Each structure stands twice: as structure tokens, then as C-alpha cells.
Image 1 (cartoon, chains in turn red, green):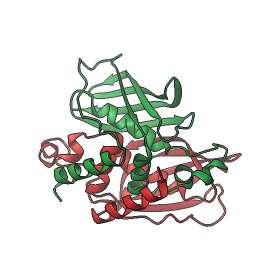
Image 2 (spheres, chains in turn green, red; image 1 turned 30 degrees about the horizontal axis):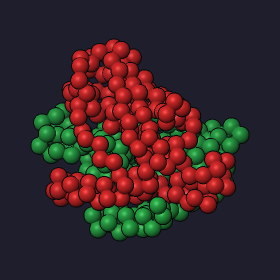
Image 3 (cartoon, helix red, strand yellow; image 1 turned 90 degrees about the vertical axis):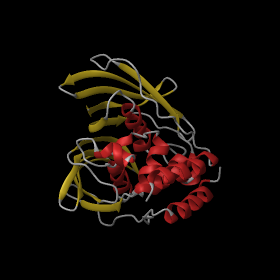
Image 4 (cartoon, chains in turn red, cyan; image 1 turned 120 degrees about the horizontal axis):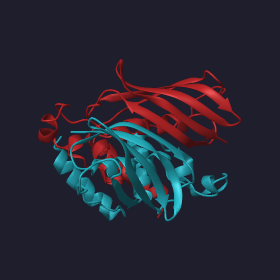
Length: 154
Length: 154
């Protein structure tokens, strides 16, 4: 499989189905304790469908408008692990080669289909080349997830 | 957007590009302390490409064979949060309507493109309708991630 060709083909299909292609641009500055960054992306139907396919998570609460409307949520919600997948994208943009070591999140409020999710991170710890980062994910001013990740940076 | 039509279209494209469509079938039995379950799925190039598109995580270490071969990994690795996305799919299959509340994972060994990842879960805690589940993810006999999730079940 030629990955670069596959990605290019899928990018075209994704964009036609309403997906937002996020350019992969590294953040700037010296990484250190207190370093802050932010990253945001809209999560639309296509993102939810693709997440369901690749994970196998076809939970009706994320897909079936009528089913979800009868639940305590009163409508569909995006997978929590799709929301937090944006944190992977955010830390991947830090200077250097970044590898995820740990993640821990609590989901605080649902994300609805079409919502823009904003990740805000701050480096709270640096031990050798392992960076501990406090993270909150938002839709507008509302916290939708909060937690901590640790990454290795080469 | 008609989600059921979009999903169906994307399922066709996904399957043609090498993706494994996992049927969504609920697990059986009474949920309780000590309840065990398992779920597995292959993660191929298409899964990685789709995860990159929907998250915006286009980290070269997951995509560029030559770049990744020069790193300490000695070749591409699947996104850690793609590996653990299978845990969402696994808990979504528990009896009832399942909502993720918390997740925490440490990544222990890389997952390579094409690897089958197996999630093994066991309910360690039940408080009202909140279930705490110890989880390990494997490729063959090798632990690739370990942690805990909490879900709400209606």
C-alpha cells in the first residue's frame, strides 16, 4: 500500500463529504514548563462516521437521531474518544518528533455533531524528554473534557 | 445530512480500501463486578489515514515510512489514540446505552500498521449505573496499552 496516495485520495473524498482538512504545521517557540498551545477543529457527520468505521464503535447514541433523542442527552453526541483524538493532533504539532505515552480524560459535557472543539494545553512537567501537559477541551466557553497527557519528544 | 446514507456510502469505500467492517452486536449476559469481555480489530493503512483526517493528526511517524524508520521506533507506528479507540467500540457493545465518562491509558509498546489489536476488559467497580472497567490492549500476547475506563450505562 502506498500510504501517501491513499491519504491523498481519502483527503479528496473527506473534503467532499464536509470534512475540514487541517494543515499539519508545527507550533513554534521553545518547549518548556509553562508552554501553552491551542488547536481546534469542527467535528461533523463524516468525522463521526469515519471514527465509527475505523474503531467499530457504531453506538446508536452517536448516529441515530431518533434513538438518541429519547436518551438523557436528548440528541446525538460525538464519541468522547473522537473529541479527545484532537488532543493527539494538538500534541503532534509540538516541535520535535512526538510520541504519546499516557492520556487521561474525564468527559464533562457532551459534544454535538457540528461543534468546533478547541484543545488548550499547557506543559506542567518536563522530565528528561517526557513532557506532562494539562489539557482542557472546549466548545465555545464550555469545558467538554479535561485531563493530562504525557508525551515523549525526540 | 442523512447520517445512515453517509455511513453506508463510507462503509463501501472503507471496505474497498482494505478496512474491516465490524458488525455492531451487543455482548450478552448480566453486567456486574467481574464481568469480562473482549473485542479485536485489525488496524490498516486506511484506518490510520482516516484517523489522521478526522483528528488532523498527520504526524509523520504514523505515515512516512522513511521518516519513521530513522526514529527509535525503526518504522511507522499506529496512533496510540487509534489503538485505544477500540476500547470505545468494546464498551459500546455492553448491554444498555453506554456513554464514556473517563478513560486513562499508558502506552507500553508500539502497534504496527496491519496489527490486530485485542481489547480485554473486566468490570472492577459498579457504583449506581457507573461501571469502572480495567482494560488491556494486546497485539498477540504483547500488552500495547493498559488502563481504566468508566462508563455510564442507561
